[PDB]
Length: 210
Image 1 (cartoon, rainbow, N blue to C red):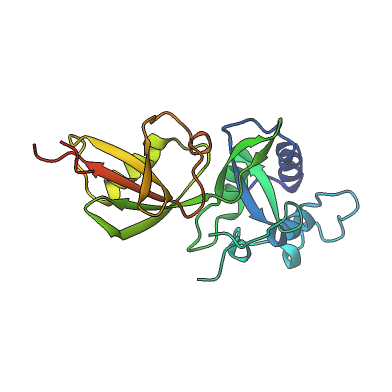
Image 2: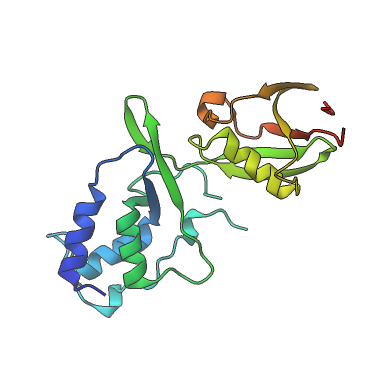
């Protein structure tokens, strides 16, 4: 691993990296980060345990951010998690390893009015294929993902061949669906929302089923 001063200095700078739309950032549990900061003497006013095995943070552990059994609700930046850009995540992973069984918590930088934010809570969609509206599978997406990305995922889940033509629809109310005709639109631009049903239909061996 880098020496403790290099870790501190690199991460101090990386925490302040400008938020640029479309960059990927990573969540780090503030419990783990607090230990890390003590161990590296991150702050001038807390070098009391710098280098001590007692505050060595061990492998990165984000289990406290994740629902028992998906992120916990009402997490607050700084208080519950900190945010690092790709380079900073990758460095921490290299130095400490990621705890066994965990996956990184990768998120995109989207717009927040005229500013930006890391999109922490993804959008869950209910996906199904027209042959059977009861065989529904849920997947999470960014609001910056495209309609094409959703369609690619549905086609994978339901084993739809690349050659079969399709039409995508979103539920608007009971038995009332609207076409998603623009594969380049983002989820934001299409107006999709949490828990919304999306259905794909394939053309028949001959025409459209729907």
